[PDB]
Image (cartoon, rainbow over all chains, first blue to last red):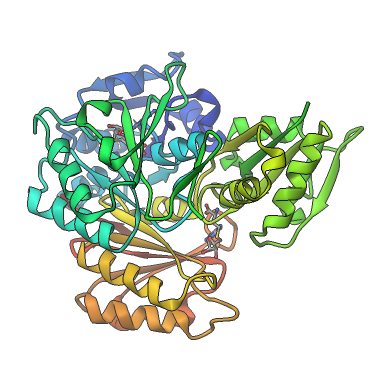
Length: 239
Length: 240
Ligand SMILES: Nc1ncnc2c1ncn2[C@@H]1O[C@H](CSCC[C@H](N)C(=O)O)[C@@H](O)[C@H]1O
Ligand SMILES: Nc1ncnc2c1ncn2[C@@H]1O[C@H](CSCC[C@H](N)C(=O)O)[C@@H](O)[C@H]1O
């Protein structure tokens, strides 16, 4: 029989793809995924490719499940970790909606997630209790974002922001900063980490009083230290 | 001219070590860490291993820096990712405390963290906003851990617990469940994921109401869902 595997490809560099993930890629008959993820995979004999847009999902996933039934071995690929604001959740949601697909074999395969690759490049800003928050979740009303931000601020968590800029919400990030400037000392360290692990990696470290929305974009993860996070030489860490 | 690399070995299975980390280990003159992690390192002329217990200490990091100054290529190893309640922090602490090693070349190499490896085995429990919390930090007063728990609860963050059963704070995880019952609905899914990616991996999902502390040990990472986090067959996920 066939299967569905949801594999994390890591933040970009090929030497971060686990050998686990590489093996499943060698077994697959089909690769489903967002255009530029699919493009990271060397084309080869017997491997049908199904690129897609970053939206939809659900049928993206139901489709993967329908292909398991015909004996196709399907890898749905994600950047970073598939369980971090990625395709793992859509699959199960698509699974709950279709009881006649329960019983297809499913495997979730972890990856180096963006925040930790960023952390590693900067030093150790996530070395204490930390949280991760999606800033382009359009199914999530803004009142919920604010409740996460404020409770992370007050609980003195280090933060990682995924999808800082939506342009669906043309700013929102502009708003996001305000809340931090309310809830945190102005010295709070802010890391703008863009295209981490790629040839165009650039990391900027800035205090909260000087943080502008323009400093983050589509290819950035924003790390926010807790109260004690500081510098040593070019590094950042949390004592 | 040497360096210090802090390298994550992932949660156990060899096929989860990144090729970048496998390559640093092949370059090391010196490995510092918990020897059972690296017992099968390929032997070769010049390779030396420095056994430590499985704990974060500043003194080994200082020593790592000292060797790098003799020109040694030092890999300091951590399970999982080294920036996650692990040795990368301590290295930067030892560096800040020893300005004489300012300028040392330092590389921090990520790995699969236990939470995301357990999340993977479970399905997608950390699919939404989540936080990571260390429950065996004896360097914090219990006060701060509590402030962290209640705010993660109130922001409706899913959560992961590292080091649930403290050897020297035996009755602490009992407090954490109490706080959780205090701040969350009874049917809040909790997952105990034991020895993830090893042949003795075992995962139990129970409601908070039904959960007891002896469900966790030191081989375990504990995942707490959002309020929405739910069950589909053997799998756990959060809808959007
Ligand atoms: N190589 C990279 N460098 C910096 N940020 C990245 C990145 N890859 C992904 N991101 C962050 O992740 C967002 C996409 S959401 C996908 C996250 C992915 N599943 C993971 O686990 O990492 C981007 O908007 C950006 O904030
Ligand atoms: N294979 C495994 N299975 C389950 N939990 C694990 C694990 N490896 C580490 N852990 C968890 O992590 C704690 C050690 S603290 C070190 C965390 C490590 N740097 C990481 O990034 O994952 C353990 O008490 C346990 O809660």
